[PDB]
Image 1 (cartoon, protein in one colour):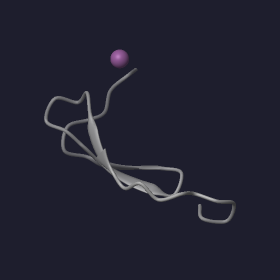
Image 2: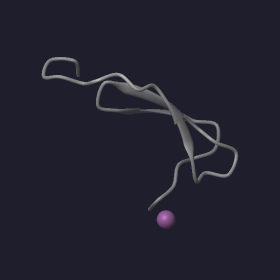
Image 3: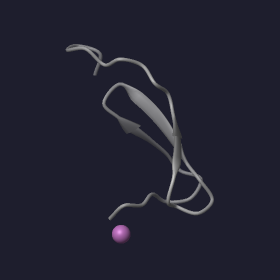
Length: 38
Ligand SMILES: [Co+2]
């Protein structure tokens, strides 16, 4: 838990994220995600 697979991308609601080298952070888009956006 509290982790991602390094260098993977993943989705969180309407946002997309790229997992850091450490697996402990991710670079994510910051879009507001209203209903229907995902
Ligand atoms: Co963990």
